[PDB]
Image (cartoon, coloured by chain):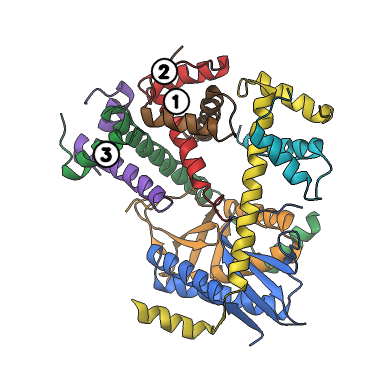
Chain colours: A brown, B red, C green, D yellow, E purple, F cyan, G orange, H blue
Amino acid sequence: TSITLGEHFDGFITSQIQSGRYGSASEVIRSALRLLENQETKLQSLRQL
Amino acid sequence: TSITLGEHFDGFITSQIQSGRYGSASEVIRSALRLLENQETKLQSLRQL
Amino acid sequence: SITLGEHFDGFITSQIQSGRYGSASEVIRSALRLLENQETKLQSLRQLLIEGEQSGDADYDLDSFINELDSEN
Amino acid sequence: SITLGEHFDGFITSQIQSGRYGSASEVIRSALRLLENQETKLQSLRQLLIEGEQSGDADYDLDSFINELDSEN
Amino acid sequence: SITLGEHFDGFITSQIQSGRYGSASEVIRSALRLLENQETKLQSLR
Amino acid sequence: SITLGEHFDGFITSQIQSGRYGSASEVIRSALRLLENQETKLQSLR
Amino acid sequence: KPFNLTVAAKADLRDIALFTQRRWGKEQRNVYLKQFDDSFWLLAENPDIGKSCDEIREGYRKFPQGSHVIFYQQTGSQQIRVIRILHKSMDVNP
Amino acid sequence: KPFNLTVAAKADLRDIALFTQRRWGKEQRNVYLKQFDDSFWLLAENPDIGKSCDEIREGYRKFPQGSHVIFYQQTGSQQIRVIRILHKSMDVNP
C-alpha cells in the first residue's frame, strides 16, 4: 500500500499535520476520503432510471 | 511514502477505480485531497483578529 | 485524438503545474465527472417535474392550507 | 482522563468500527475541528455585525434605491 | 493523453449521440469549461 | 485515547475558560454532538 | 382560481412550511407562506416574469423564491400551473 | 422612517440585488427588493417577530429571508435598525 502524491499535496499534508489540527499523515487522507465518500454517496440520483 | 488506510476505505477506493470514473488509486486520493484543501482554504475567516 | 484550443490546453497545463492534478488525463477525467454529475442532476430534475405534473391538481388556498397545518400539530 | 457517557462512548466505537475513523483520538479530533470551525464562524459573524453597526446609517428608500441601481447600468 | 476509461469513452459518445454537441472535442471542452468555472469560483475565495 | 495535540489541548482550555462550558468533558461531548448531528444529516441521505 | 398547484407541489410547500416552522416558528411559517402565495398570484397575473427553461422541459418556466425555485407551466394568458417547488438542485445549462 | 439601514446593510442589499439581476433579470431584482422592503416594514411594525439571538451579540434579533438572514436591533416600540443582511453563514448555538 503506497501512493505517489504530488509535491504540492505532500506539502499540504505536512502543513496540515504541522497545523496541530491533524495527528498523523494518514488522518488527513482519511478526512479527505470522508469528504469524497460523502460527495459520491450523495450522488444516488444516478439510480432514477 | 505510504499510508495505512482502513479496510473500508481501501474497498471504497477499489470501488471508485472499478466504477470507471477514476483511473488510478492515487487519482481518488488526489480528488479527496482537492476537496479537503478547498474546505480548509475556505476557512480563512480564522484571520479576523 | 482531439483539439481543444490554446485556452483549454493552457488551462490543463496550469492545472497540472499546480500539483492538484497529476496527469492531463486526470484533469480531463475530473471535468468529465463534473459534466456527468450535472447530466444526472438534469435528468433528476426532469423526473421530478414529470412525477409532479402527472400527479393530480391539488385543492390549494392559502388560509385553508394554514388551517390544515395548524390542525396537524 | 475524561468521562462522556454511554451515548458518546457507544458512538465513538461505532464510528471506529465503520472504518471511517482509525483511532478514537481521530474521531475526537474531527469533532474538535468541527467545534473550532463553528467558533471561528461565530466570531466572524460577530465581527461582521460590529463592522456593520459602527458604520453610518444609510439613507434608504426602496424606489430611490431601485433608481440608483438602474442608473448604475 | 487520450487514455481515458471505457466509462468516459462511452459517455462522450452517448452525449454526442444526443445532438446538442458536435463531437468529443466539444464535450471535453465544455467539461473543462465547467471545471474552469468551478476553479474560478474558488479564485474569488483565494 | 487522551493523546490529543497541543493545539486541541490549548483550545479546550481556552473555551472552558470562557464560562459557557464546565470542563474538557463537556466541550468534547458537545463537539462529538456536532459530529453526530453531521453524521445524522448524512443518514437521512443514506 | 388563476393558479393551481399539483399534489407534488403542495407536498413540497408543506415540507418547506414544516421545515421553517420547526426551525424558526409558526408566525415565520405564516409570513413565508404568505410570500409564496403572493408569488403565486404574481406569476398568475404576469406569467412572462419567469425565465423560460425549455432546455430542461418543453414549456416550463422557473422563478426564484429564497432557497427554492418554483417551476410552472403557462396554461393561459393569465393562468399558470405550479408543478414543483424544489431547492437549489437546479442547473442553468444555457 | 420606522426602520433604517446601515452603510454595510445597504451594501449587502446592493450586492444581493446585483447578483439576482445578473442571474435572473431586472424585474426579478425589483420583485426581490420589494419583498425585503416589505420584510423591513414588517420587522418595523412588529419587532418581536425575529427570533432573539443575544448569544451571538447582546440585543440583536435575526429573521430569515430566502437565502439571506436580516440582523436587526430593536431601537423602539415599533422602530428597528437593520445592521446586516448576510447569507447562510450563520449558526444557532442554542
G70 and C28: which is toward the camera? C28
Residue at 38%, 53% in the rendered image: G92
G36 and A28: which is toward the camera? A28
Disc 1 crowd rating (10 Å Cα; few below 14, some 14-19, many 20+) is many
The chain identifier of the residue carrying mark 2 reads A
Rendered location of residue G10, percent (x, y): 62, 56
Which amino acid, by three-letter code, is at mark 3?
A: Ser
Residue at 45%, 33% in the rendered image: A12
Which amino acid, by three-letter code, is at mark 2?
A: Ile
Work out which residue is located at the far bottom of the displayed protein and give it.
H1
The answer to whether residue G14 is above or below residue H28 is above
The chain identifier of the residue carrying mark 3 reads C
The residue labelled by disc 3 is C14
The chain identifier of the residue carrying mark 1 reads B
Rendered location of residue A45, percent (x, y): 49, 36
Disc 2 crowd rating (10 Å Cα; few below 14, some 14-19, many 20+) is some
The answer to whether residue F8 is above or below residue A30 is below
Q: As drawn, is G22 to the left or to the right of C30?
A: right
The residue labelled by disc 1 is B29
C26 and G71: which is toward the camera? C26
Give how far apart the Cα atoms at labels 3 and 1 are: 20 Å
The answer to whether residue C40 is above or below residue E4 is below
Rendered location of residue D29, percent (x, y): 65, 32
Q: As drawn, is F4 to the left or to the right of G73?
A: right
Residue at 46%, 75% in the rendered image: H30
Q: Are marks 1 and 2 in contact (CB under 8 Å)?
A: yes
Q: As drawn, is E34 to the left or to the right of H62?
A: left
Q: Quadrant of the N terminus of chain B?
A: top left
Dot 2: element: loop
The residue labelled by disc 2 is A3
Q: Are marks 3 and 1 in contact (CB under 8 Å)?
A: no
Which amino acid, by three-letter code, is at mark 1?
A: Ile
